[PDB]
Amino acid sequence: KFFERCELARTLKRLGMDGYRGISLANWMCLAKWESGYNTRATNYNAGDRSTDYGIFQINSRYWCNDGKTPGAVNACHLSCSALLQDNIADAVACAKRVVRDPQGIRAWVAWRNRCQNRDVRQYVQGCGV
């Protein structure tokens, strides 16, 4: 499913993302926007290392979820990567939270550094009631 902006903002807020480990909701929105355009079914195969990015946050199969076809991969969120392809983003949010508990925090995603870090992200939550 492709979420509408504010619909996603409140969906994320209800899931406990607002300020999670110091990360504002607008930051998560910016992340999902640039990672998948708010598309829960987004997938990107990385032919270079044989891994695949799954869902709204484009979480990688090498370390976070298990798809059974990524060489020497681990599964830190302890989830089938299929769980990251659901319209319901609860499992994807649980995994995104797992990612940010690591030292890098939100910096785990290169796209966040490229398109959200030190950017005016207010636009993502304006008028959403969050």
Image (cartoon, rainbow, N blue to C red):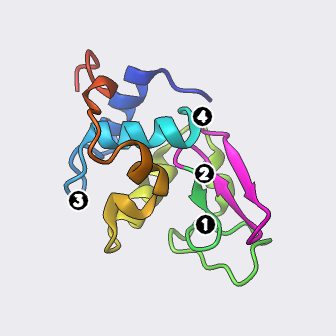
Q: Does dot 1 land on a helix, a strand or a loop?
A: loop
Which of disc 2 and disc 4 is earlier in sequence? Answer: 4
**Mark 1 and mark 3 residues within 8 Å of each other at the beta carbon:** no
Instruction: Say which residue label 2 marks.
Output: 84
N-terminal of the two: label 4 or label 1? 4
- The amino acid sitting under disc 2 is Leu
Q: Nearer the viewer, mark 4 or mark 1?
A: 4
Q: Dot 3 corresponds to which residue?
A: 21
Q: Range of the magenta residues?
A: 39-57
Q: Which of marks 2 and 1 is nearer the N terminus?
A: 1
| Dot 2 and dot 1 residues touching (CB under 8 Å) | yes
Q: In this image, 104 relative to 68: left or right?
A: left
Disc 3 or 4, which lies upstream in sequence? 3
Q: Is residue 108 above or below residue 13?
A: below
What is the crowding at mark 2: few (fewer than 14 residues within 10 Å), some, or many (at least 20)?
many
Q: Which residue corresponds to mark 4?
A: 39
- Residue 33 in picture, x, y percent from top left: 48, 35
Could you tell me which secondary element the residue under label 4 belongs to?
Answer: loop
Report the residue marked by disc 1.
65
Which label sits in the foreground, 3 or 2? Answer: 3
Instruction: Give the position of the C terminus as an image quadrant.
Output: top left
Give the CA distance from mark 1 to mark 3.
Answer: 21 Å
Residue ID at (39%, 53%)? 113
122 above or below 86? above
